[PDB]
Image: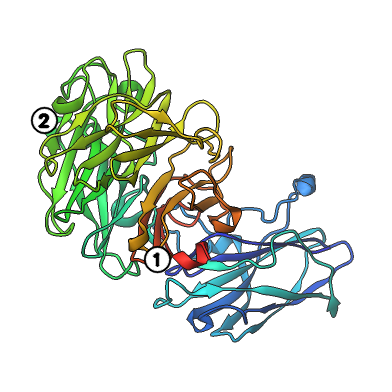
Amino acid sequence: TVFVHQTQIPILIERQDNVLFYFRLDAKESRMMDEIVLDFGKSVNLSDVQAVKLYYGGTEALQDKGKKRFAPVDYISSHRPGNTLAAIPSYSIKCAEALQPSAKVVLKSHYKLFPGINFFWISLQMKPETSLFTKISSELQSVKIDGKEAICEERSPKDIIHRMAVGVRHAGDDGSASFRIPGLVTSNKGTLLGVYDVRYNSSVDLQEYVDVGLSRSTDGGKTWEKMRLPLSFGEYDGLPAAQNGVGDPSILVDTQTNTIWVVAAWTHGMGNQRAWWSSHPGMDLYQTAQLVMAKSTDDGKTWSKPINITEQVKDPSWYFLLQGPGRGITMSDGTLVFPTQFIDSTRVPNAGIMYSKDRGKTWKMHNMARTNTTEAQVVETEPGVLMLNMRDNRGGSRAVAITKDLGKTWTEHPSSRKALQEPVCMASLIHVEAEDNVLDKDILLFSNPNTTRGRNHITIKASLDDGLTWLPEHQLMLDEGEGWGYSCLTMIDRETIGILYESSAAHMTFQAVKLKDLIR
């Protein structure tokens, strides 16, 4: 009797509903759902909560009792264009509400049960001005059925903390079906800058009507400005906009000048097919994907015309050359570095880096880090030494490599193919210097789906010993839900981590986490 699951998924601040708990019972001997009691004392900033709601979901198909679902369907969608904010009315009947609650919330349903499986769920609704650092605790006190307490089975953790998030981009925003590839940095002015594919027609990759979009925050990621487009080719050379896609962007800040650079892959032509199969050897727009960039010198507010750098660094034998999605870095000595990946003449992906020594006028690549690798992120552990963490096509474990010569030679790391599990997905790696964080320690931050299979359990991890060890104690999982998996970390300020990722709640989900919360 009474099976309970508490969610560990971001709570979107602007959402009208958020899934907090699921409930399932086979009503063999049970007549009426009387009430459900929860304690929110333990939350910080309980005042931020607009409402807590109880909803009746369905019953189940008789043949499917063994599936032991906690719901018959997803009650809220992150994919329905322009319909991601409220519970889908036809899937759920609201049976109780608690407005501006104190610690003790009683949800009085008094709801006739179906003779068989019965589903219920609780919804959390925040106020618009909710703080990013608001934390909601919701401890289940009791479930009453027929005038008396029922036995509950709750296999989910009891110490869950529901964290806040903003859906920077939701499905359907500004006429676009989807938003996919996140990149996040912090400017010298402290300005947050999020870039992504805006995939207008569908969620499909590479060749399609795709621009790279940008969201900019001047308040620590609490609010975001109207979307900008750093890169957009339209009907270039008289090909349809869907044959001029540009996406999979990466972003870096030039810490010497605050110039912001975004690099992306411009694919010309190729019909309606995947550019991973469609880009062919050669050098021009007729033949092969173009490596193009834009720059901002006014803190991300406006952007230059595109700059095609394909000639500078692309080997014509290669099928496909593009940045590694996410972010790049300015080194100690002022060098600019972007992770790279190319499909060679044998059709094998290889991760590497490219660099500019002249504020981004000219770029240069040496050699690959490892064969059969794709998306990577790169970090400077000490001056002159770069660590390349890479999506590895073999098994499910991040590959790591080291270069002290900007990619001429590579040294495998002790952690490579062992310390960080992946389902073969993008991962984010950043490095923070002691003087730049309140822990006065040197740390590697990492975020990815924490599994070998499935894109879910997006998890932030920290290392204190140069990426040798990643202690459970210094991890935090944000989203147990199924999503697209990509993420990008940044330091918001000296005490605060930022994350922009594809969650199960929203295509572009932003969350802020105090450094001390993660590490301690």
| Residue at image mark 2 | 237
What SS does tag 1 mark? strand
Residue at 24% from the left image edge and 57% from the top image edge: 227
Q: Quadrant of residue 31?
A: bottom right
Residue 503 horizontal/vertical position (percent): 47, 53
Residue 496: x, y in percent? 39, 66
Kind of element beneath mark 2: helix
Q: CA distance from mark 1 to mark 2?
A: 45 Å
Apparent side of residue 365 relative to residue 145 in the rendered image (left or right): left
Q: Is residue 322 something one can see in this rendering?
A: yes
- The percent position of residue 457, horizontal first and vertical second, equals 56, 50
> Which residue: 57% across, 40% down?
454
Q: Dot 2, how many residues are within 10 Å of its Cα: few (below 14), some (14-19), or many (20+)? A: few
Say which residue label 1 marks: 496
Instruction: Name which quarter of the figure residue 24 lies in.
Output: bottom right
| Mark closest to the chain's N terminus, 1 or 2 | 2
